[PDB]
Image 1 (cartoon, each protein chain N blue to C red):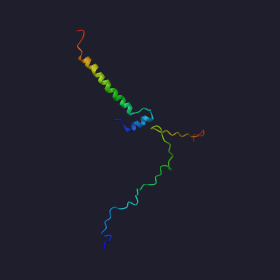
Image 2: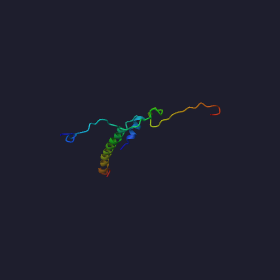
Image 3: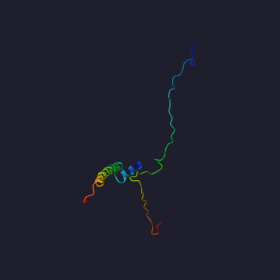
Image 4: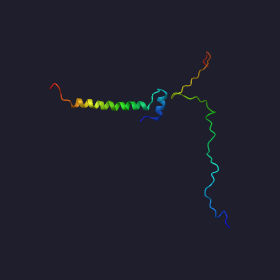
Length: 53
Length: 51
């Protein structure tokens, strides 16, 4: 009685591949504007009182 | 032996080509030295004049 014990399996079917990578949030979290020079100078400009606060 | 982080700096800030600047000073240096050689084998190999 030939059964699946006689038959020999050549290869597995590849089915599914999985690479585990985080949902990556640097895009939503931080305010990004590319810099065209190796040093990046953000101004910030403060509207004061006569008391400087 | 110029850094890979240099060219990007120097392309961005100065617009110069990095590589093509070193290839500028090496290609010029050898032809300046090979030329400083023969002038220095003329003044080396020349007899003393006014003698």
